[PDB]
Image: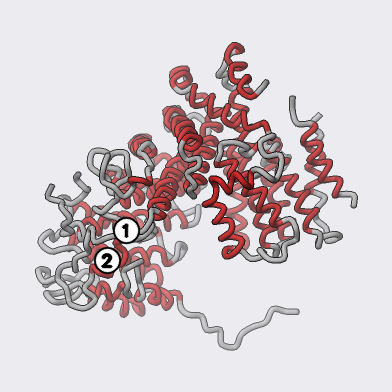
Amino acid sequence: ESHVKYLDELILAIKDLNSGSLKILNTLIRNLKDQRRNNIMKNDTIFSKTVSALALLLEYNPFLLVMKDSNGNFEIQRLIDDFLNISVLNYDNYHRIWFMRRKLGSWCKACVEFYGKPAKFQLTAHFENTMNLYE
Amino acid sequence: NMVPLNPNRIIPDETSLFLESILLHQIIGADLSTIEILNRLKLDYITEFKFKNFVIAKGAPIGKSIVSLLLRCKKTLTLDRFIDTLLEDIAVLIKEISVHPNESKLAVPFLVALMYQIVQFRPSATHNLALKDCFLFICDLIRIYHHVLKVPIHVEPQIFQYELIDYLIISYSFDLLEGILRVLQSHPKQTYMEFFDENILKSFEFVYKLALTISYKPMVNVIFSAVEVVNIITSIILNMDNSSDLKSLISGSWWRDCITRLYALLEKEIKSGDVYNENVDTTTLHMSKYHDFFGLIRNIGDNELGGLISKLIYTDRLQSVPRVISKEDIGFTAPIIGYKMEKWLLKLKDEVLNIFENLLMIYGDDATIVNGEMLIHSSKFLSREQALMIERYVGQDSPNLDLRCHLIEHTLTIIYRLWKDHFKQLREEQIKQVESQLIMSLWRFLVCQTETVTANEREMRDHRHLVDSLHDLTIKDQASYYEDAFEDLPEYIEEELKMQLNKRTGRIMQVKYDEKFQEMARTILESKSFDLTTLEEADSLYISMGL
C-alpha cells in the first residue's frame, strides 16, 4: 500500500543520509504514530519490516534518545512505553514479541549504555514501577 | 461478560506449600528429601542441645530434630517468622557443630541447603531482618571453624576427610551467602537500608578476602559464590533509590578492597582444555578432582559430586560421620562440561565486568571508584578478549564464542560511557598507559563499517556452517524445541532468524558488528571529548579501511 514503500524508502534514506538536515526525527515520529492499526494487522510482514527498519534506525540513532523529549526525561522512555502499547495491541505473536523485545534491547538499552545514571534510572523507575503497577 | 467466581476457592497455604518445598528439599544428586538427608545425621559427642526447643543427644539425628521443628513450627510460626526461626535455630546448630571441631559437620552443608530452600522460598515473604541474621550466623560459624576457614594450598592425596565435610559445607555456605544476598536483591527497592549495616558489609568484606584467595588456591565454586555476592551487593546498590545512604555505608575502602581482587579475578584465565585441572594455579580455574559440584544454585555442569551428595548420607544406615563422597571416583565422556564451564566462568567474568559497567553508570560523575584505574584494567579486558576471540576463539566452534562476544561488547559499553562523560578522573598517565587498547577498541568496530562483508545470503550462512556450527545447532534446537511458532511461519519469523544468526556469527568474527557498536567505538575517536590521535595519527588508522 502506502507504507510498504514507507519502510523501503525508510531504509533507502537511512542509507542515503547516512554520513560522509536530520529529518530522521519526523520519520521517527511518523513510525511511532503509524503502527497502531488493525487495517492490515494480519500482514505481519510489512509491520515487521517497518518496525525492524525502525530498529536499525534507532540503532543508527542512539543520540536521538538523548534529545530529552519534553516530559521530565529523555526520548528513551517515551519511546519504549509507546513500544509496549503497540505490543499490547499485538500481544500474542511469539516471535513478533521475541524480535520486538530484542529491538527494545537494541534501542532503549543502547540509550542507557551510551549515557549513565540518568538514562539508567529513567528506565528503571518506569519498569520497576510498572511491575508494581500490574501487581 | 463479568469475571466469574468460585464456591470453594481452595488455596494451599503459603506455609503449606512451604513445607512442601522444605520437606521434599532436594539438591541435584542428593537423591532425597533433604529433610530425610538431615534425618541421617546423628551426633554422639553433643548429647545436650536446645535453642528454641532443639533437643539433640548421642544417637539422636540432626534431622530428627529438624523434622521436629519443621512440623510444630508450621502451626506455631508464620511464613517469615518460620523462616527466621529456622535460620536462627538451625544456625545455632550450624555454630555449635562448627565450634565443635571434635565432631564432623555433615550437618552444616544440608542444613545450609535447607537454609536455601528457606531463603529462596519467596523474596517478598522472606524478611530482611532474618536475612541479615542468617549471614551473621554464617560468619560466626566460619569463625568457629577458624582452622578450616579457607582452602590453604601433600597431606591431600585423594582423601575426602574434611574435604567432603568442612570444605563441602564451605561451598554450600558460600552459595548460601550468594542466594541470601540475591533474595536481598529481590527485596523491593525501598527497604534495603536495614540490611545495609557495616556489620554485614565488613563480615562480607572478610569472607570475600577469604574466598578470592589470591595466595591460596581458591576453590572456584567458592570464587563463583563470592563474585555473585559482590554482584548482588552492587545490584541492591543500583536499586535503593536513596542510593546515597548505601553508598555512604559501603566504604571507598570496601569498593577498592573488593574491585581489586575482582581485577585479579577477571585476569585469571578461562581455559577449557585445563579447567578441571589443578596445574598452573592463580590462572587456570582448577575446581578439578579436588572439589567440583553444584552447591545451592550453581549448575556447575556435570554436578559430579551431585549424586555423591546423596552418597554423603548412607541412605541405608544411621551414620555419625559422613558416608565417603569419593573425591576422584568422580567423572568425563567429552568436554561439553569443560565447554559449559568456559561459558560458566565466562558468565563469572561477565558478572565482574557487569557490576563494573554498572558502577560506571550510577557513579557517572566524579567518583573515588571511577578512578580510571577502572579504565586501565577494563579496557585491558576489552582489547585482550577481542584479541583472544579474533585469534583463537575463531574456528573453535564453541557456544563460549557468544559469551566472549558478550564480554567484549559490554566492556566496550563500560569504557565508552567512561570516554563520553567521565574524563574528570582521567589524566595523561592513564591516557598513554592505555591508549592502544582504547584506540583499537575503536578501530575494531570502525573497520566493520564496510557492510560489503555479507551484503547477501549465500556467504554468512556458510560462515556459520564453518565456525558457528554450535550455535547453529542451537538455533535448530530452538526451531525444534524451545519456541512455539516454528511452524507455518508468516514469512518474517524465519527471515529474522537468518538475519539474526548471520549477524550473530559475524559478531563472533569481530566483523559486521552491530552498527550501534560500530558507532559506539567510532565516537570515542572522532568525537573530541578526548582527541586520542593527533592529525598525524588519526589518518594512520583511517587508512586501514580506506578513508
Are marks 1 and 2 in one subunit? yes
Left or right: where B497 falls relative to B196: right
Which secondary structure, mark 2?
A: helix
Q: Residue furthest top?
A: B536
B532 left or right, relative to A30: left
Determine crowd level at label 1: few under 14, some 14-19, many 20+ residues with C-alpha closer than 10 A: many
Up-down relation of residue B304 to residue B73 (above or below): above
Residue kind at label 2, given as amino acid type: Leu
B455 horizontally vs A4: left or right: left
Query: Which disc is residue B293 wearing?
Result: 1
Please, what secondary structure does the residue beneath circle 1 have? loop
Residue at 59% x, 16% y is B540
The quadrant in which residue B302 appears is bottom left
The chain letter for the residue carrying disc 2 is: B
Name which residue lies at 31% across and 69% down: B30
Residue B345 screen position, x and y as percent: 40, 47
* Residue occupying the point 64% across, 50% down: A102
Question: Residue reaching furthest right?
Answer: A1
Q: Earlier in the sequence, mark 1 or mark 2?
A: 1
Residue B22 drawn above or below residue A9: below
Confirm or deny contact between disc 1 and disc 2 (CB under 8 A).
yes
- Residue at far bottom of view: B7
What x and y, as percent, mark residue A12? 81, 38
Instruction: Let me know if residue A93 appears in the view.
Output: yes
Per the image, the residue denoted by label 2 is B308
Quadrant housing residue B17: bottom left
Kindly tell me whether residue A122 is visible in this rendering.
no
